[PDB]
Length: 569
Ligand code: FES
Ligand SMILES: [Mg+2]
Image (cartoon, rainbow, N blue to C red; front, side):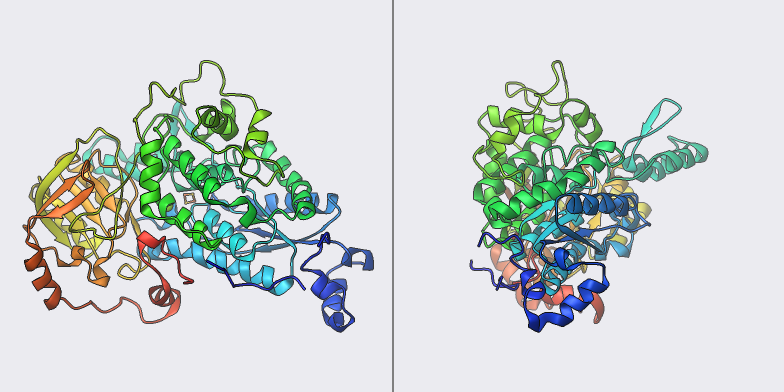
């Protein structure tokens, strides 16, 4: 598609956009403001870099990003350019998890994209350096870069370090699990409170291979971050050094005029996907990479993810699936060492251009390989799973697609009577009151999609409640929303069409025999197509849960999960 969104420049000029306001006499107003903010006449000749951080104080993932932003600005000035900082909003999935505040999470990606697009366009900045630090922030910044197509680099804020106390390790997942362990009797209240005080020891994104590190790693593999960006910890002095170098790299991108639509291509999108499959990355990457692909006028379907999943084995022994965390990847050569191995295996396209001004292959020629003896990244001949974790399922109940994380440890089939709930809350009340009624069932939590939720909330409490009741492998879990963790069993999200839109998931009744088949890739119902059609004629959409504000705008704008929940088409 031909993307028309933002202003064109008015060709070896480095100030292609800012010249619109710095050069003409008829933009004297603009120049007056710029003198006011501290620019000399000589400064007006230089390129202007929009430096977009997602700093805020109330989240560990984001509290350090103002300091990083200052270091990016200093490096832009050291590279002979003007650096102009601005800052957008973000939200904390870790804070808002288990609450209605989670309805505002996914849409913050799209709000972030709109924010950066807005400032870059209005202020006529020539290039962008973005400093996201948390889940949704990362793709939001890349989407903005794709829309604008101005030279850009994403500096990942970096991963949090695991907490340590009295020779035990903790992360955010320890803190989530602590409640269930207390209720079951596995730990005391004092041990519970100890976990909370030592789970998050400083700044940076959640530590394992959840969405932040998945997306950071993916975006490095896509060529839109500098080498090591995804693997250097937040509090590591090298992160600050990377910040101070971004300016030098971006200067070179302006000389080359190497733009996001030159770097983000079908092949580099594939490279990103390869990294998700190899590292055991989150199912959320499906939504985010589709959104990134659309931002540059390219197509990316659920089927494309299945093909890359089938082609690429799961190799990384990393949480949540495995043992180690993102800090351990840093110790054995970082993300470049991982990607170097995948390139040597023939799994990636080396000729894709990157933000270094060189190709992926060129970047990876000159990096140390995975440390001899390391046990984190398995060899090709002994993978953790022969294909990727990410599985696309269709069938009667998800005719437009759905996404699941499949380890290989759960078997190929599950069949059981449907147990249907109209939101998360009613599911949690039922399993609390009568846990044994869930045994052998296919649990359906519906009305939690993009429009129905609203906001397509991510839900953790259902899987942990199932685990806490001892029913992990003894029931399946289906939703039009999203789930956070694995149940050691069949857990499917992103079911399309969502129940709010009258998809078959909205027509399921209690007792319907639902059969999940992984080999066939189908979520089927024993109810006849005719009886499902009769139910469809009786069905009417429930009223929207909001009538005003940002979530009502989301309801009006958002596309399906199968289309990456894009809001601007
Ligand atoms: S709440 Fe920020 S990456 Fe988890
Ligand atoms: Mg999340």
